[PDB]
Image (tube, coloured by chain):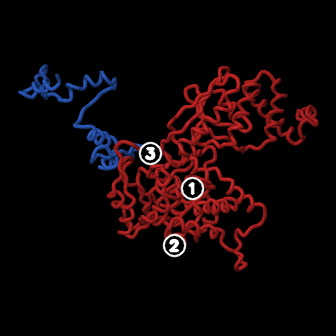
Amino acid sequence: QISKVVEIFAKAYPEIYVVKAAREVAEKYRKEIIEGARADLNGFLEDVERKIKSLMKPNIKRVINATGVVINTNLGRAPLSKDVINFISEIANGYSNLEYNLEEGKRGSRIAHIEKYLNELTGAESSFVVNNNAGAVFLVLNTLAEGKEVIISRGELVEIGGSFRIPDIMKKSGAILREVGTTNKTKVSDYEGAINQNTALLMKVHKSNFYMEGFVEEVKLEDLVKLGHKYGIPTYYDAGSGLLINLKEFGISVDEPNFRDCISLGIDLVSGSGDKLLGGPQAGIIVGKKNLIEKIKKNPIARALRIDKLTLSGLEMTLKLYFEKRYEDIPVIRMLTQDEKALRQKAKRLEKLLKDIPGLKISVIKDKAKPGGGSLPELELPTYCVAIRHDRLSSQELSRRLRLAEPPIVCRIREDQLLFDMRTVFHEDLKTIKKTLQELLSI
Amino acid sequence: DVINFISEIANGYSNLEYNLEEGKRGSRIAHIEKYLNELTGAESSFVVNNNAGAVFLVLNTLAEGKEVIISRGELVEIGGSFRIPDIMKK
């Protein structure tokens, strides 16, 4: 019973956790024994103690990312420069002029603090910001095309993440969905073909987390705009990457689309996540024509999507950085634009820390990985891994224990050889890497 | 080898639509199908001009006016005028 387990650990662990550890372990042996899968009760003493050790720590923990994927959906997307985290810390520490204008001394709209930055950086007439890009979509449809049709290419009906899908959202959006062209190809005649009285919207979505090769055709963006200005229809581009600037300017050569460029091209509305290529905290970012934004703003779901104090502040600081050309300060930009050189530099500095540890086979390989996970699907870039192999322990079991470390470490596996992509690894992590390994193979 | 076998059948008359046994017309599809049933292992078989029309046939035979469910990822445009949605319509 739970009272005997409270007697076994008196001062050992606080009474509150011990009973929550006996209640979860006791439902686990009640169901394992009912199903007839357990013949021994002896593991009960150690496991109620491991639960207590575990239940006494946070579920969400910082993790050292070895995979060399900058934008790791599973690992928390764009991490944040300390500068920013500090400004977020300060604003959360007490009250703040969130919804308060200091000039007039009367309430004010919280989305007003930021928008000045967006409209300067992109060039759009006005702007706005909601919970994530997801809702930013759901908002631009339900606002603009409730009960009327929207035209989109059959190749752009994406499923990104686990629950999101343009057709399943747009439906619930209340917009009527008109799918032109074919999977692989879509000409301009396909869009123009389906125009009619009901058509309220010309939407294009960017294939963020996939890509098609082979015989493939797509509708030029200059073309969608010409088309809409013909029949008097608004265009709506879901970047999704929400890349904020031209990326070629950093030496990486891709066609990824960005706010500034897409707007000056003549699209009427653009959106994208903030926790992607922008580098910030999670946010739906929407920019374009004044008359449209106003309309979005006034829709009463906007209040159900409006951003929290934490992501609001933190977004301002990241926007600040971007105005100050302080690029290297926003993690997701530095990690992609890191010099091939620089990577090696780090690679061998690590190797140097592990030489001494027993049983460790350590080598430095130059590999081609694909860094972007949720925003740059075709991108392939050279990065140096430190592959390691232990005589006593196998690569699989290695990863596993590394994931259970404090802090935990997550990495790629490849042909029974553990790898460490240096693209995503922070310096202060190296010392913690060495201490982790030596605690595992010497214990 | 092929081209010769073709050349030869083309240089004169042939039992194309003619069954020699019964001395009566026969289906031209009949010559081939025996090979197809053996190689594939299906119950029966048939042949038409090209795959394009083979799709068109199987839809219009089996689904005229009824629903055909297909993956949104599989609606292709192969070649310049063949498109599964465009033909499936017709």
Q: Split into 4 quadrants, where in the image is the C terminus of chain A?
A: top right
The tag earlier along the polypeptide, 1 or 2, is 1
Residue A394 image point, x, y percent = 64, 23
Which kind of residue does numbered mark 2 sit on? Lys
- Residue at the (71%, 72%) spot, across then down: A100
Q: Which chain is red?
A: A
Q: Which residue is mark 1?
A: A278
- Give the chain of mark 2: A
Residue placed most toward the observer, A254 or B30: A254
**Answer yes or no: do the residues labelled 1 and 3 have beta carbons within 8 Å?**
no
- Residue A243, above or below A56: below
Q: Which chain is blue?
A: B
Q: Which residue is mark 2?
A: A290
Which kind of residue does numbered mark 3 sit on? Tyr
Q: Split into 4 quadrants, where in the image is the N terminus of chain A?
A: top right
The tag earlier along the polypeptide, 1 or 3, is 3
**Element class at badge 2:** helix
- Give the chain of mark 1: A
Residue placed most toward the observer, A281 or B52: A281
- Residue A428, above or below A359: below
Are labels 1 and 3 on one chain?
yes
Residue A378 image point, x, y percent = 46, 44
Residue placed most toward the observer, A161 or A260: A260
Residue A181 image point, x, y percent = 36, 52
**Answer yes or no: do the residues labelled 2 and 3 have beta carbons within 8 Å?**
no
